[PDB]
Amino acid sequence: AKEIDVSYVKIEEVIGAGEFGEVCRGRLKAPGKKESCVAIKTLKGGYTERQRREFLSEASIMGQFEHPNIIRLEGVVTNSMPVMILTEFMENGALDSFLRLNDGQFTVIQLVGMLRGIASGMRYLAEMSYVHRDLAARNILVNSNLVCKVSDFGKIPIRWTAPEAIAFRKFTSASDVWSYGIVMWEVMSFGERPYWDMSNQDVINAIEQDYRLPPPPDCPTSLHQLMLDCWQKDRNARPRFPQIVSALDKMIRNPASLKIVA
Protein backbone atom coordinates (compact mmCIF):
# COMPACT_ATOMS: atom_id res chain seq x y z
CA ALA A 1 0.00 0.00 0.00
CA LYS A 2 2.69 2.47 -1.11
CA GLU A 3 5.06 1.64 1.71
CA ILE A 4 8.08 3.85 1.32
CA ASP A 5 11.68 3.53 2.46
CA VAL A 6 12.47 5.97 5.29
CA SER A 7 15.78 6.83 3.62
CA TYR A 8 13.78 8.50 0.83
CA VAL A 9 12.18 11.01 3.26
CA LYS A 10 13.75 14.19 4.68
CA ILE A 11 11.78 16.26 7.22
CA GLU A 12 12.51 19.97 6.80
CA GLU A 13 10.30 21.98 9.19
CA VAL A 14 7.28 21.61 11.50
CA ILE A 15 4.41 23.53 9.90
CA GLY A 16 1.28 22.54 11.83
CA ALA A 17 -0.44 20.35 14.38
CA GLY A 18 -2.84 17.52 13.56
CA GLU A 19 -5.15 15.19 15.44
CA PHE A 20 -2.38 12.67 16.17
CA GLY A 21 0.74 14.86 16.23
CA GLU A 22 2.87 17.21 14.15
CA VAL A 23 2.58 18.10 10.47
CA CYS A 24 5.86 18.81 8.67
CA ARG A 25 7.13 19.94 5.29
CA GLY A 26 9.66 17.65 3.70
CA ARG A 27 11.24 16.15 0.61
CA LEU A 28 10.60 12.77 -1.03
CA LYS A 29 13.30 11.37 -3.35
CA ALA A 30 12.88 7.80 -4.67
CA PRO A 31 15.17 5.95 -7.12
CA GLY A 32 14.38 6.86 -10.72
CA LYS A 33 12.10 9.73 -9.68
CA LYS A 34 12.60 13.47 -9.34
CA GLU A 35 12.51 14.91 -5.82
CA SER A 36 9.15 16.35 -4.74
CA CYS A 37 7.79 18.38 -1.85
CA VAL A 38 5.53 16.55 0.61
CA ALA A 39 3.49 17.16 3.71
CA ILE A 40 4.40 14.64 6.42
CA LYS A 41 2.16 13.58 9.33
CA THR A 42 3.96 11.73 12.13
CA LEU A 43 2.65 9.51 14.92
CA LYS A 44 4.95 9.18 17.93
CA GLY A 45 5.01 9.44 21.70
CA GLY A 46 3.57 6.20 23.09
CA TYR A 47 0.18 5.76 21.44
CA THR A 48 -2.33 2.94 21.54
CA GLU A 49 -2.62 0.37 18.79
CA ARG A 50 -6.17 1.59 18.13
CA GLN A 51 -4.92 5.13 17.64
CA ARG A 52 -2.31 3.77 15.21
CA ARG A 53 -4.96 2.10 13.09
CA GLU A 54 -7.13 5.20 13.23
CA PHE A 55 -4.17 7.31 12.10
CA LEU A 56 -3.40 5.00 9.18
CA SER A 57 -7.06 4.62 8.18
CA GLU A 58 -6.76 8.05 6.55
CA ALA A 59 -4.08 6.75 4.18
CA SER A 60 -6.15 3.66 3.35
CA ILE A 61 -9.09 5.86 2.34
CA MET A 62 -7.09 8.60 0.60
CA GLY A 63 -5.21 6.03 -1.49
CA GLN A 64 -8.46 4.87 -3.10
CA PHE A 65 -8.83 8.22 -4.91
CA GLU A 66 -7.16 9.93 -7.88
CA HIS A 67 -8.43 13.40 -8.87
CA PRO A 68 -6.90 16.91 -9.19
CA ASN A 69 -9.13 18.33 -6.42
CA ILE A 70 -8.56 15.47 -3.92
CA ILE A 71 -5.37 15.44 -1.81
CA ARG A 72 -2.93 12.89 -3.27
CA LEU A 73 -1.33 10.19 -1.11
CA GLU A 74 2.39 9.76 -1.78
CA GLY A 75 2.74 6.86 0.63
CA VAL A 76 3.25 5.64 4.17
CA VAL A 77 5.98 4.60 6.59
CA THR A 78 4.68 1.73 8.75
CA ASN A 79 7.59 -0.74 8.96
CA SER A 80 9.57 1.71 11.14
CA MET A 81 9.07 4.50 13.66
CA PRO A 82 7.75 7.04 13.77
CA VAL A 83 4.77 6.08 11.61
CA MET A 84 4.29 8.56 8.76
CA ILE A 85 1.73 9.55 6.13
CA LEU A 86 3.09 11.53 3.16
CA THR A 87 0.78 13.64 0.95
CA GLU A 88 1.21 16.32 -1.69
CA PHE A 89 2.35 19.64 -0.22
CA MET A 90 -0.19 22.53 -0.17
CA GLU A 91 1.69 25.81 0.18
CA ASN A 92 -1.28 27.96 1.33
CA GLY A 93 -2.69 25.62 3.95
CA ALA A 94 -6.33 25.52 5.03
CA LEU A 95 -8.79 27.57 3.02
CA ASP A 96 -10.59 29.28 5.93
CA SER A 97 -7.43 30.75 7.46
CA PHE A 98 -5.98 31.52 4.00
CA LEU A 99 -9.03 33.64 3.14
CA ARG A 100 -9.01 35.40 6.52
CA LEU A 101 -5.38 36.40 5.88
CA ASN A 102 -6.42 37.72 2.46
CA ASP A 103 -9.77 39.34 3.34
CA GLY A 104 -11.17 41.26 0.37
CA GLN A 105 -8.06 40.58 -1.73
CA PHE A 106 -9.29 38.01 -4.30
CA THR A 107 -11.86 38.75 -7.01
CA VAL A 108 -15.30 37.17 -7.28
CA ILE A 109 -14.10 35.15 -10.29
CA GLN A 110 -11.15 33.80 -8.28
CA LEU A 111 -13.49 32.80 -5.43
CA VAL A 112 -15.85 31.08 -7.90
CA GLY A 113 -12.86 29.18 -9.31
CA MET A 114 -12.01 27.92 -5.82
CA LEU A 115 -15.62 26.82 -5.31
CA ARG A 116 -15.63 25.07 -8.70
CA GLY A 117 -12.57 23.02 -7.73
CA ILE A 118 -14.14 22.01 -4.43
CA ALA A 119 -17.37 21.04 -6.22
CA SER A 120 -15.41 18.97 -8.75
CA GLY A 121 -13.71 17.07 -5.93
CA MET A 122 -17.08 16.40 -4.34
CA ARG A 123 -18.61 15.38 -7.70
CA TYR A 124 -15.88 12.72 -7.89
CA LEU A 125 -16.38 11.52 -4.30
CA ALA A 126 -20.14 11.18 -4.84
CA GLU A 127 -19.52 9.21 -8.04
CA MET A 128 -17.22 6.88 -6.03
CA SER A 129 -20.05 6.46 -3.45
CA TYR A 130 -17.96 8.18 -0.75
CA VAL A 131 -19.80 10.42 1.73
CA HIS A 132 -17.41 12.89 3.38
CA ARG A 133 -19.52 13.95 6.44
CA ASP A 134 -17.18 16.83 7.46
CA LEU A 135 -17.04 19.11 4.41
CA ALA A 136 -15.95 22.54 5.71
CA ALA A 137 -13.45 25.19 4.60
CA ARG A 138 -11.05 24.11 7.37
CA ASN A 139 -10.84 20.73 5.58
CA ILE A 140 -10.02 22.23 2.15
CA LEU A 141 -6.31 22.79 1.34
CA VAL A 142 -4.91 25.38 -1.09
CA ASN A 143 -1.81 25.16 -3.31
CA SER A 144 0.45 27.92 -4.67
CA ASN A 145 -1.74 28.26 -7.79
CA LEU A 146 -4.93 28.63 -5.63
CA VAL A 147 -6.16 25.13 -6.54
CA CYS A 148 -8.43 23.86 -3.75
CA LYS A 149 -8.48 20.18 -2.76
CA VAL A 150 -10.65 18.15 -0.40
CA SER A 151 -8.83 16.62 2.58
CA ASP A 152 -9.56 14.85 5.90
CA PHE A 153 -10.44 11.24 5.09
CA GLY A 154 -9.60 9.57 8.42
CA LYS A 155 -18.59 14.87 17.52
CA ILE A 156 -20.93 15.82 14.67
CA PRO A 157 -19.96 19.23 13.17
CA ILE A 158 -23.37 20.74 13.80
CA ARG A 159 -23.22 23.98 11.85
CA TRP A 160 -22.01 22.19 8.69
CA THR A 161 -24.48 19.29 8.93
CA ALA A 162 -27.82 18.79 7.17
CA PRO A 163 -30.86 18.61 9.49
CA GLU A 164 -31.76 15.02 8.61
CA ALA A 165 -28.18 13.94 9.34
CA ILE A 166 -28.29 15.65 12.75
CA ALA A 167 -31.72 14.23 13.57
CA PHE A 168 -31.49 10.70 12.13
CA ARG A 169 -27.76 10.09 11.40
CA LYS A 170 -28.55 9.55 7.71
CA PHE A 171 -25.47 10.81 5.86
CA THR A 172 -25.62 10.87 2.05
CA SER A 173 -24.15 12.87 -0.82
CA ALA A 174 -27.22 15.11 -0.44
CA SER A 175 -26.16 15.88 3.14
CA ASP A 176 -22.69 16.72 1.77
CA VAL A 177 -24.45 19.15 -0.61
CA TRP A 178 -25.87 21.01 2.40
CA SER A 179 -22.33 21.21 3.81
CA TYR A 180 -21.06 22.46 0.43
CA GLY A 181 -23.53 25.36 0.66
CA ILE A 182 -22.02 26.25 4.03
CA VAL A 183 -18.54 26.16 2.39
CA MET A 184 -19.76 28.54 -0.33
CA TRP A 185 -20.83 30.95 2.43
CA GLU A 186 -17.45 30.62 4.17
CA VAL A 187 -15.62 31.39 0.91
CA MET A 188 -17.72 34.40 -0.07
CA SER A 189 -17.31 35.76 3.48
CA PHE A 190 -13.51 35.33 3.44
CA GLY A 191 -13.55 32.79 6.28
CA GLU A 192 -16.21 34.05 8.68
CA ARG A 193 -17.60 31.46 11.11
CA PRO A 194 -21.01 30.07 10.04
CA TYR A 195 -23.81 31.43 12.26
CA TRP A 196 -21.34 33.64 14.17
CA ASP A 197 -21.88 33.33 17.94
CA MET A 198 -25.02 31.15 17.90
CA SER A 199 -24.81 27.95 19.93
CA ASN A 200 -25.18 24.50 18.38
CA GLN A 201 -28.73 24.09 19.67
CA ASP A 202 -29.59 27.64 18.54
CA VAL A 203 -28.44 26.68 15.03
CA ILE A 204 -30.51 23.46 15.04
CA ASN A 205 -33.61 25.35 16.16
CA ALA A 206 -33.15 28.24 13.72
CA ILE A 207 -32.74 25.93 10.70
CA GLU A 208 -35.87 24.00 11.71
CA GLN A 209 -37.62 27.39 12.02
CA ASP A 210 -36.68 28.36 8.42
CA TYR A 211 -33.72 30.67 9.09
CA ARG A 212 -30.92 30.58 6.52
CA LEU A 213 -27.63 32.48 6.48
CA PRO A 214 -27.83 35.80 4.57
CA PRO A 215 -25.69 36.81 1.57
CA PRO A 216 -22.16 37.83 2.57
CA PRO A 217 -21.16 41.43 1.82
CA ASP A 218 -20.75 41.98 -1.94
CA CYS A 219 -21.85 38.40 -2.69
CA PRO A 220 -23.51 37.97 -6.12
CA THR A 221 -27.18 37.10 -5.73
CA SER A 222 -26.79 34.09 -8.04
CA LEU A 223 -24.23 32.58 -5.65
CA HIS A 224 -26.47 33.13 -2.62
CA GLN A 225 -29.40 31.55 -4.46
CA LEU A 226 -27.23 28.47 -5.09
CA MET A 227 -26.51 28.37 -1.34
CA LEU A 228 -30.27 28.45 -0.62
CA ASP A 229 -30.78 25.58 -3.09
CA CYS A 230 -28.20 23.49 -1.22
CA TRP A 231 -30.03 24.29 2.04
CA GLN A 232 -33.47 22.96 1.12
CA LYS A 233 -34.95 20.98 4.00
CA ASP A 234 -36.06 18.17 1.66
CA ARG A 235 -32.80 16.42 0.77
CA ASN A 236 -34.27 15.19 -2.52
CA ALA A 237 -34.85 18.78 -3.69
CA ARG A 238 -31.19 19.82 -3.35
CA PRO A 239 -29.03 19.93 -6.50
CA ARG A 240 -26.57 17.09 -7.01
CA PHE A 241 -22.83 17.78 -7.38
CA PRO A 242 -22.82 17.52 -11.21
CA GLN A 243 -25.49 20.25 -11.32
CA ILE A 244 -23.50 22.43 -8.91
CA VAL A 245 -20.37 22.20 -11.09
CA SER A 246 -22.43 23.06 -14.18
CA ALA A 247 -23.92 26.15 -12.50
CA LEU A 248 -20.49 27.42 -11.45
CA ASP A 249 -19.11 26.78 -14.95
CA LYS A 250 -21.90 28.95 -16.37
CA MET A 251 -20.99 31.80 -14.00
CA ILE A 252 -17.35 31.59 -15.13
CA ARG A 253 -18.45 31.68 -18.80
CA ASN A 254 -20.89 34.57 -18.18
CA PRO A 255 -19.11 36.76 -15.60
CA ALA A 256 -21.51 39.63 -16.29
CA SER A 257 -24.15 37.57 -14.43
CA LEU A 258 -22.17 37.95 -11.17
CA LYS A 259 -22.73 41.73 -11.10
CA ILE A 260 -26.16 41.65 -9.42
CA VAL A 261 -25.71 42.11 -5.66
CA ALA A 262 -28.38 42.77 -3.02
Image (cartoon, rainbow, N blue to C red):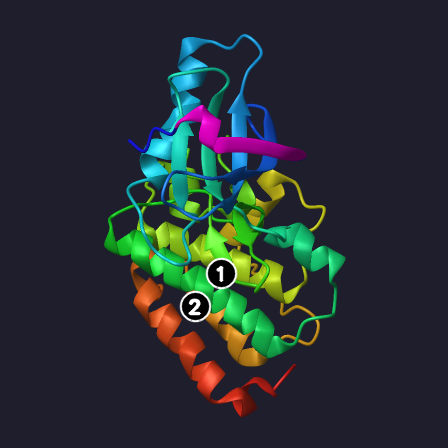
Query: Could you classify mark 2 by the number of other residues whose Cα lies within 10 Å: few (under 14), some (14-19), or many (20 or more)?
Result: some
In the rendered image, is residue 194 in sight?
A: no
Q: Please state which of residues 135 and 33 is positioned toward the viewer in this rendering.
A: 33
- Give x and y (percent) for residue 27: 54, 39
If the image is split into quadrants, where does the C terminus sit?
Answer: bottom right
Rendered position, 185 above or below 109:
above
Secondary structure, magenta segment, majority class: strand
**Residue 13 within the magenta-colored segment of the rendering:** yes
Q: Secondary structure at mark 2?
A: helix
Marks 1 and 2, how far apart at CA: 8 Å
Residue stretch rendered in magenta on the structure: 5-14
If the image is split into quadrants, where does the N terminus sit?
Answer: top left
Q: Residue at x 61, y 58 (%)?
A: 186
Q: Report which residue position mark 1 lands on.
A: 181
Q: Report which residue position mark 2 lands on.
A: 229
Q: Residue at x 37, y 56 (%)?
A: 122
Q: Quadrant of residue 73?
A: top left
Rendered position, 95 above or below 202:
below
The answer to whether the residues at label 1 and label 2 have Cβ atoms under 8 Å apart is: yes
In the rendered image, is residue 63 in sight?
A: yes
